[PDB]
Image 1 (spheres, rainbow, N blue to C red):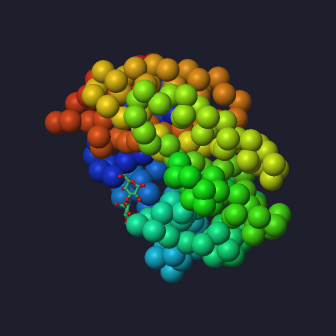
Image 2: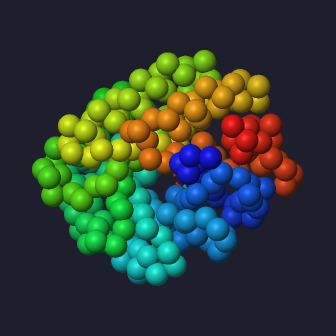
Length: 230
Ligand SMILES: OC[C@H]1O[C@@H](O[C@@H]2[C@@H](O)[C@H](O)O[C@H](CO)[C@H]2O)[C@H](O)[C@@H](O)[C@@H]1O
């Protein structure tokens, strides 16, 4: 396909269901892959402050095993996720992500689609505290909501692209998106947004949320099959 489509996983043993599809890349919300999967670029994630102790080793290991991208904190805007102030994330990004910029493309912390001061509000606060000192190759963003809200998904992704552009960051990865409903509604959502993302110059990569919901009893669900085939 486009080369944009990724596999976001928990159970590594479910990636096999997707073997041969138009998938370039994977991530697992962890700094280490939990094994090896041939033919796919694994992208390590510095999920939050619990990861600081191992991160330099984890990043070097990922670079040596062929990773060319690194992701920063997972939903620092959400207190049940990485739970970090914009100021804290800007300092930690400069400490833990910037040193890898010569050898890996670096993704921003990934924000939710919450209203300000969460979501892209948080992201703008983070890009303000960075003050040009964070080496950011792309913004990472998340959108979850009903399958009928395509309009709101596109609105959110366009808003993220525009925000990146105000701070000299050309492109985004949509590292989680989920058009929610029954399997039929989920497939209709993918039929609408997958082509839209594939032709969007602003979006480098994306991952429908997520491999372990798209696989039941070893088999792609109708939603997993649409993710493989659209
Ligand atoms: O199990 C590995 C890591 O899983 C994390 O949960 C992920 C969320 O952060 C994310 O937004 O959703 C995915 C899929 O539901 C979750 O795997 C934990 O919060 C980490 O503690 C955990 O190490």
